[PDB]
Image (cartoon, rainbow, N blue to C red; front, side, top):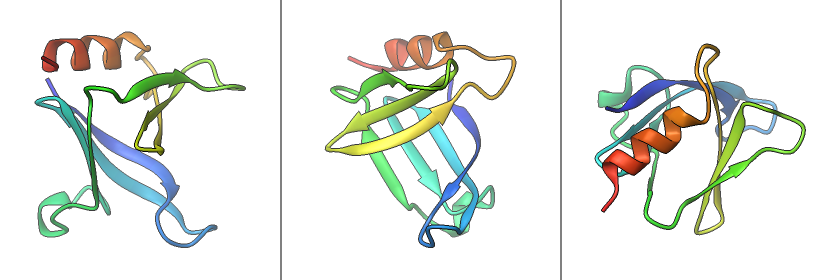
Length: 94
């Protein structure tokens, strides 16, 4: 299953943090400007084959997805844990 949710982080403006729509499915992570996704097309997309799930420093539930130096600061929504990403990618990957 895809993890589809909004991630509050900057898009273009350094102080222009907004809710961007991220989807983790198939074996790729894709993000759009916001939850309206489809009309935005695609803003970014990485392949979860060598994208390392890096546990964040100060955060216990935040996980930085790093591939091609593209660091995706993800986090467990609230009732979630790391295993969301693990199980998802593990069940998506080849």
